[PDB]
Figure 1 (cartoon, rainbow over the protein chains, first blue to last red):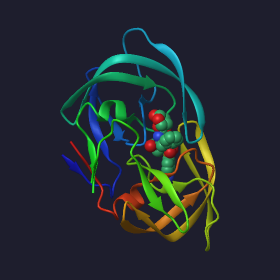
Figure 2 (cartoon, each protein chain N blue to C red):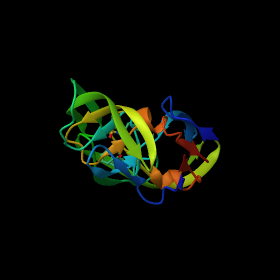
Figure 3 (cartoon, rainbow over the protein chains, first blue to last red):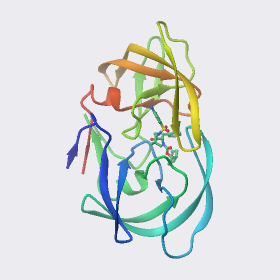
Figure 4 (cartoon, rainbow over the protein chains, first blue to last red):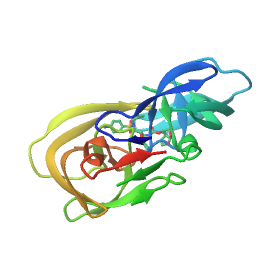
Length: 99
Length: 99
Ligand SMILES: CC(C)CN(C[C@@H](O)[C@H](Cc1ccccc1)NC(=O)O[C@H]1CO[C@H]2OCC[C@H]21)S(=O)(=O)c1ccc(N)cc1
């Protein structure tokens, strides 16, 4: 799709068979979801944003479907204000900025 | 232009006698720049993201030039680690997400 930016670019995603809303976020290097259960091993990690650093759980090679487009990559779980799809997955679905 | 997302979407912007690098950020509601001393009236504000909140000054009707495209609107100023062009100005320069 072509998505304009008068509203937040929130899209429904499928992750672990569950539907969630997430923000397409070109200023995020990484993908972070609010607290949820994901299967398999995770690695403790820390990441920084505008307001400081947080601790997250890093899950590798997680399939996610974003508006019907498949990605498989790293998903962090931690105290983000909203679920965010970052460039690690936006690149996999072929997303670009255009003006 | 078309900007891919393999790397951070940093572009040159002009805000006064300052040429700066800023992130084209679909996950940011409003433009926020690193500490600088802009002219007019303003309003204190707190903006939140990963790690918590920062205090900023909100300035209105500030003209900026983004890759040669003119914009004019709200610019927040505060201790952000990265200059960010948010949706408030991305819309004005005709920027969309496409996949
Ligand atoms: C978390 C988002 C809902 C909101 N943020 C914009 C977001 O794009 C920031 C923008 C950003 C970019 C770099 C540094 C700080 C903030 N990215 C971010 O936090 O990404 C994190 C996940 O991937 C990592 O890569 C970048 C930081 C990590 S925000 O910076 O907090 C923000 C919030 C409000 C406004 N008006 C402007 C910006």
